[PDB]
Length: 108
Ligand SMILES: CCCCCCCCCCCCCCCC(=O)O
Image (cartoon, rainbow, N blue to C red; front, side, top):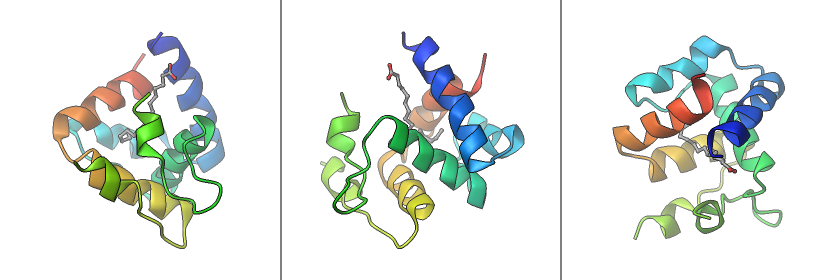
């Protein structure tokens, strides 16, 4: 850990969402991927680590952790992929955080 579990997580979510490596690789400069399929990849990551609220569909950011946590953890849209994308946009606003998760999941 942490590299072995995250690689395991990346391969399943590429397959489920149907997002290309090119679409996800946009994260390398700190950008949160925007493809309709890459937004679903993010939902897949939250679903596999069990941080998607059964009752509301909101992302349980406090659980994910192990001032901004509260607002970003109450975002709910009619689309599961849009909900996950909007939550990441809200919470991981700094370029450095996106890059760190990008490297952990996406590179060898
Ligand atoms: C690259 C997408 C944008 C920002 C990142 C979104 C949050 C993804 C969270 C996945 C973290 C994986 C770490 C799991 C490690 C473990 O369980 O031991």
